[PDB]
Amino acid sequence: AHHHHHHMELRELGATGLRVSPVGFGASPLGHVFGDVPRDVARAAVRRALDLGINFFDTSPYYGGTVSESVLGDCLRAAGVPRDRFVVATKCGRYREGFDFSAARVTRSVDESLARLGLDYVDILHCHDIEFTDLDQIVNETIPVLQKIKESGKARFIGITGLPLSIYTYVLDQVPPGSVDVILSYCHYGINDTALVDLLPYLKSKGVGVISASPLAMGLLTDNGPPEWHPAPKELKLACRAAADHCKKKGKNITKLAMQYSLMNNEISTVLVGMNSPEQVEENVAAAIELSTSGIDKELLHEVEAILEPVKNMTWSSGIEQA
Ligand SMILES: [Mg+2]
Image 1: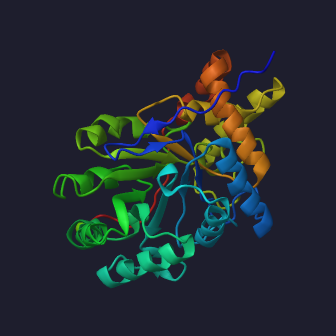
Image 2 (image 1 turned 60 degrees about the vertical axis):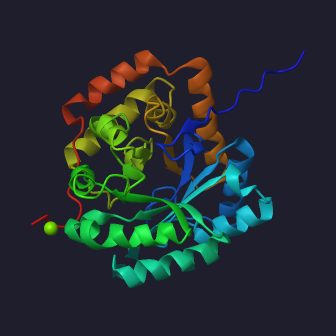
Image 3 (image 1 turned 180 degrees about the vertical axis):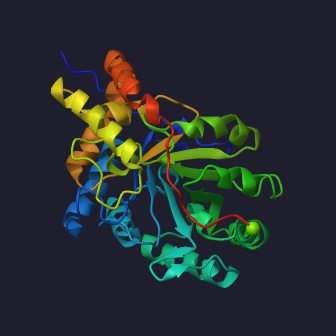
């Protein structure tokens, strides 16, 4: 006899032609609740992800965890992965010293990112956290500039990211069709908040691919709970603590349940997870394969959904007023 080897099933990303693993390797916010790791651990996490079939890596030039553009670049170089077998996204506009979405900064940004990544092009270049600028700048200036960067061949596809779902309608209503290829949304496709679903037809109709992130809502859907800085309302924090406790008391793990839940909508091509160590990679890939072969625990899910119902889709402010 032998054991059957199940693998993740790739998803098609928008109209890009890219086929991406349903679990993607993302960044972590500063001060995330796992804590940082040494560079050797970060490199081993990326290697483990490549070895388990993750083929989508998201990074940025801004603060995160130990996994950075330079770490990704070194790991990809060392692994020798064929370029058409993995997908890399980076971002521009958000830096440690502040936001700068101007034409000269982002044009320079891309070149810096490419050197760190050891690539001639990125698959995706996103405008990062655009709710922190006047969205008309993104419409009138930054997306035009990224068209030039795409035409240069240094980025194949252009994206926009941020927290409030209203940024995507504001921008995508006001740029020429085809100007944006993908979006990255976070915190809006997980058990406590699925509001991204309300944009999926819209995005499809505009030929925009969909990437989601933060399936555990930056630590809400964990046993440990969120970091002290987390801007969720206390009412949401309380409900997520009750949901985690509900799972724990029964010998189950909310993180696994939450990861699997976020994977249950195939109109989202990849769900990015901030992973810090090989073990976290192993756990998330197993959750995704188990979803595919054994199913989610539906009764536990229904119970957790009832706990979270009063706070479903509750969010928090981000960025400036659009005036
Ligand atoms: Mg404005």
